[PDB]
Image (spheres, coloured by chain):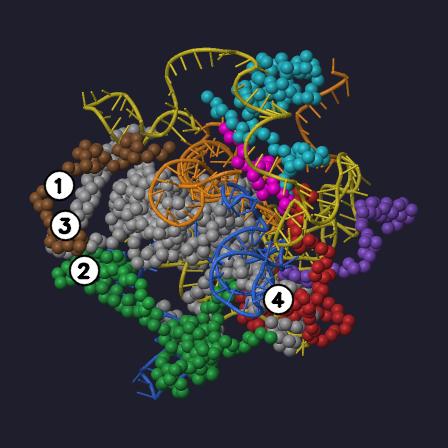
Chain colours: C brown, D cyan, E purple, G green, H red, I yellow, J blue, K orange
Amino acid sequence: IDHTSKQHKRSSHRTAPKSDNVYLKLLVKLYAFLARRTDAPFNKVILKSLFLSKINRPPVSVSRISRALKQEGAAQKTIVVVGTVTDDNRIFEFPKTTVAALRFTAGAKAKILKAGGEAITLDQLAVRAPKGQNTLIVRGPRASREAARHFGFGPHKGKAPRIQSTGRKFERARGRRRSRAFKV
Amino acid sequence: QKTAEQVAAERVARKAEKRAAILERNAAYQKEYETAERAVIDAKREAKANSSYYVSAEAKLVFVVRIKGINKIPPKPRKVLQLLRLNQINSGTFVKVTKATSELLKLIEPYVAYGYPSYSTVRQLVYKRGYGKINKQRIPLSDNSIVEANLGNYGILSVDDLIHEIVTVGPHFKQANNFLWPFKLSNPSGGWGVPRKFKHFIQGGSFGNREEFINKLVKSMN
Amino acid sequence: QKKNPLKNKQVLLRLNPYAKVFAAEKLGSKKVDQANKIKPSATALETLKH
Amino acid sequence: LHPKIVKKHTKKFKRHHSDRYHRVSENWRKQKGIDSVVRRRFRGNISEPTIGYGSNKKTKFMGPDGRKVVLVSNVKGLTPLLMHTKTFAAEIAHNVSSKNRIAILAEAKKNGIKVTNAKARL
Amino acid sequence: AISKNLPILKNHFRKHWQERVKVHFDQAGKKVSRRHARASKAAKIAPRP
Amino acid sequence: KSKNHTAHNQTKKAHRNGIKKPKTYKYPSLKGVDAKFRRNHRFALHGTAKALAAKRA
Amino acid sequence: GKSHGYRSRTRYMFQRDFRKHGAIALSTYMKVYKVGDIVDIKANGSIHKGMPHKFYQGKTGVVYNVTKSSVGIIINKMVGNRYLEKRLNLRVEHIKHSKCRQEFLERVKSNAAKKAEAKAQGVAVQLKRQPAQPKESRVVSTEGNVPQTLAPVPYETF
Amino acid sequence: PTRLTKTRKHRGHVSAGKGRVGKHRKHPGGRGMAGGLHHHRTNLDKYHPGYFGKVGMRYFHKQQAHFWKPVLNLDKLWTLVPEEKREEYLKSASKSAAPVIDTLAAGYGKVLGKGRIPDVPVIVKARFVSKLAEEKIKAAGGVVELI
RNA sequence: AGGAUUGCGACUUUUGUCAAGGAUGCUGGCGUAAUGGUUAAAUGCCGCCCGUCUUGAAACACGGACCAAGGAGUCUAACGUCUAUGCGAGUGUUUGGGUGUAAAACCCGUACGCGUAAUGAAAGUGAACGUAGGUGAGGGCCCGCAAGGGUGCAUCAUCG
RNA sequence: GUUGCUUAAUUGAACGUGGACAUUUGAAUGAAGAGCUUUUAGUGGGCCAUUUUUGGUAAGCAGAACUGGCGAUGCGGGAU
RNA sequence: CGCUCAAGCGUGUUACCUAUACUCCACCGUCAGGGUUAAUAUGAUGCCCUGACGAGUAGGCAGGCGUGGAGGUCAGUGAC
């Protein structure tokens, strides 16, 4: 038989979480039910994000949440993070807001609830909004990681070499400048 | 729970309207084929009286069959067989005949036998070995409710209406032919009428163009 | 179990409602045709026979 | 009406050269050879175990009776099989003493539970 | 000897290092010896710090 | 004694993985372009930024 | 040793022509090149400055930069199992305009005329290009055109 | 865990994940960075550069003590002041009563400009300062004392 | 094969009937070594001796008389990608001290390592014109009966 | 509209602001989902066939070109 | 083996034999696309539906079977 494509191919996606956590899999069952039933695009996005790894779920700073509120016509939207929400000390006037996430830090709990906010978890959000109405999903920065700078090293890529320490006398002389042979 | 019992009486009444629409259309298509055959036969007799030769219109539709099996096939003809959906040995399709499609058949002529079918061989293939492509998944054409659900936007509200598009070569041949899954045929019951299968029809073998004799070969395999 | 329209007949009549009208009037036969003219030739038989 | 059992391949898969040399036991073991004919599948040689020989899912782990066997060592271990006589049969262990078999066999026959062994030494 | 895309390490283990290895199993037991020594000294000296 | 060179199973290897086109983008890479042109081009984009800012008022 | 120079195996490629030696006609220099035009390449044996390597004879590419005497042309070439972008700098004497894109611009204007004209009259356009269809039926007249009976000739020695 | 490794799974097969032709011999290439200039040049031309050679001049008896000076951005600045005394100070200090921020006690050398601080008088104490860092503090109201 | 019903239909004046989304009906013999299971021999056809290096082994290529037990990718110091867990601009109790049912379990904190700033050989200097900037793509949400418009995180390209 | 480029210039050239034209997304056929990233194994002695072909009297000899096989592969036929 | 108006050589026309190939049905596994605890006992890792595919050395990953010791648990089995 002329096999055009590969046979018995895998889906190439995380179906369920690799984690064995009891409380997380309860949250999966709730959103997995909604994604089949509701027919609201919001629910199918949050179903994907619960399956992700620690690298694929970066931390969202509270200053990043404050920027999205300045968008023209998005003052009272329930901002749904899928990860951790860390505190930030490069800002002062944090407004009265409502947030939804898996985890909140000890600092970020105080910063929201001092202004008079609502630190909600994803199950409590699902009671108010099944379809996801007047929501606003936020995702943290992937490619600012210490491993990301070393990927795809070579001539003349403009990337960082994998080394321990540190300044001169360590990957500087021959092959990095015209005085000593050449500049890569 | 309640009123859904009354819907059983209702929903049946709307299908009685559709069966009348199928019956009148099938009567119209029968009148098209009978007039098409009689017009060509009498037109020859018209020309023969006035010291002239009627030349018939060239074939608008052709049916291909994979003869050679797998392996030891060069890459260029192997690519063309992949495009015409003849991946397995003994496989059908139908091809809308153009100048462009004729050049594809020249490349793969040792590995296939092909000719011009009629409203008879086409009727048997779509009933006995007919299968539809419905969100992938090779699903059979048991009921005509399946064909209306998918191909309802281009007319084609029945199995015979799908057959009409294949035979006449209408504007929606490209959509209607691609809907059909390639016909997985059996080996011929009588035989190939030869000692050797790979020599071209006119010399002795099976492959290449055979025009009128493809109808006999398919009915045995059907 | 996929039946087959050619055999069985109830599956045939599930499709093509015209199968009654085809079979009753005998359209796989149809008398048919015609005098007026057995209508002949001119110089075709000279080239054909030669 | 219970599905009739078909075993596909009843003959035992012996290892290659088990009868030839004494040290090679009859427990199955895959040939990892390059000259080997058992790996490459030649005509007129021993068969190999393959997933195609697997039994039907309707009738798996069932004997001639049509019952899945459970191992029992005492009277308290009979309490899962009280309302499941047609589906689950019992079997008493080898390490149980002679007098304790009479204790299990007595209360087993009350509820109508079929034991594969016993019989019971005598 | 070398070659993927890994950092160039510096492991100084080309002498007879296995002959001169120490493992501190005594950490837990040696703590009690010091607490015993500090206590027994205070008993000898008595009223002084 | 040893074989020198060949190109057998070479094109067959290449077509397994891909043989791909070079992607293409809108706004291509502006490298190896005339330096006198680029300096004036910078001042044009700076000036037109002032124009659109004044319009929105 | 093996020879792998810059102008290796260029005996007939950079050979000039039959009865077209010497100077070049002035229309070569007069032609205009804006950033975007498609152009085919032909090396000229007489002009030695800004000369292309043998591989790019007959290749086609888009112009990206323009200067005093030259034009920058990016050409995609195959190597290993992956296409790479390459940047050339050839003088005006070698480059000429491509006539492949020429026919496309004729088709754009004609379709716009047919859509605008027919919508206020016909209500039926048919603007997609048709492949060469098969024949229709017809009748051939035999009056003063009677068939000539042929036969295969016997073998002779010239 | 000894059971989870792949050497348990290889029991039965001859080569054990090393091939029949390659054999797995002792030291085919060398022993650690051997032949860097000869037959491992293609590895070191890629991936590393600047490996061989020597840039710069020597320092005899160098001490990590003269070279100290840990930096501090103006973004952080207010973190040195306590958490209780913050909502109080941010709302009305207004001169003659500004919160003194000694950077050296916390452990910082050079006060350094980056962030955009709020308009409150500060009075900072530090060893070193940037030119931009002083401009931002004077715009607010305060001053910089040297030590 | 399947194992309540649901669907498409046909024949029906009608109720109903049916070859219509996979076999039901009626009858006989035996109720056990008779049917099956393993095991040994006979008969038909087929079957060269394993392991190994090799483009290539039944080989006139190497090891193997036979059996039992033993017998071969382990542990460590620095590390890379991916994954789970805890806290998160911080993080790390266990050098050491306090206690104790005593190598355990529990508690304590100055330092110090890595991270929060880079670039230069060094002397050194040291990251907001603008809503932390525009353009093209972008999931999701918002307005709308729709057509379409508004707002656009991650990321990719691109000019500042 | 934009400028320090270019013009005898109120020209040109790049990047734009607003505007008109979506059945007829402007050849055929197919699409098995498309694009992309990290990481690491074995391998780096090859050989035979149909045409093209160099050395050689010629070779189950040596050496290249294009597809297909064996090596990694049983099964029916060529007795083997 | 034996064959001579062949059981030989060239050519034609029919029947017939037959592969793990082709068509159809049963069962196994792998992969994909769906449907469902809306109290509704027993494994949501469940319970069903539909469609395709299956050779393989060097190599990689997955799911299981067994051996010697350690913590828990069946108030497990045993001079009957």
User: Do labels 4 and 2 touch, CB within 8 Å?
Assistant: no
CA gap between label 4 and label 3 equals 84 Å
**Chain letter of disc 3 in the image:** B
Membership of H76 in magenta stretch = no
The residue under the point 27% across, 60% down is G152
Give above or below for J42 relative to F56. Answer: above
Disc 1 marks which residue?
C33
The dot on residue B45 is 3
The residue under the point 81% across, 56% down is E17
Give above or below for B201 relative to G38. Answer: above
CA gap between label 3 and label 1 equals 15 Å
Dot 4 amino acid type? Lys
Q: Residues within 10 Å of mark 2 (few under 14, many from 20)?
A: few
Position in image of residue H10 (x %, y %): 66, 45
Disc 2 marks which residue?
G147
Disc 4 marks which residue?
H46
User: Which element carries disc 1, helix, strand or loop?
Assistant: loop
Mark in the foreground, 4 or 3:
3
User: Do labels 1 and 4 touch, CB within 8 Å?
Assistant: no
- The segment highlighted magenta reads D33-60
Dot 3 amino acid type? Arg
The residue under the point 32% across, 69% down is G158
Position in image of residue A15 (x %, y %): 50, 45
**Chain letter of disc 2 in the image:** G
For the question of whether residue B98 can be seen, the reply is: yes
**Chain letter of disc 4 in the image:** H
